[PDB]
Image (cartoon, rainbow over all chains, first blue to last red; front, side, top):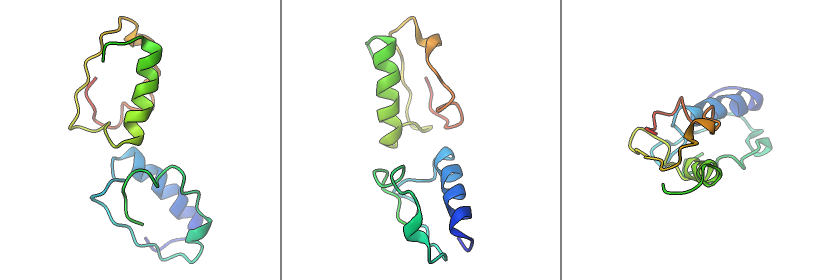
Length: 49
Length: 49
């Protein structure tokens, strides 16, 4: 995902809704502000970010 | 799931967290108050309830 960290926070929520935050998916983020993302909703799921 | 509808609301949240609300899972509910459950978090996911 090449996009701002605000876009990235938004697209992750949609990805969860879509059954795409699981061990099958690996997401590389272009943003340097990745560390700013609330990651509480996703760390238990097994996705790779 | 044989349990009260309040238990069922609770166990569904845990099932979501666990990557178990998807098209692979089919849940039959014993409770007659199934229709009382907030189903907004789950209807887009493809689970069968």
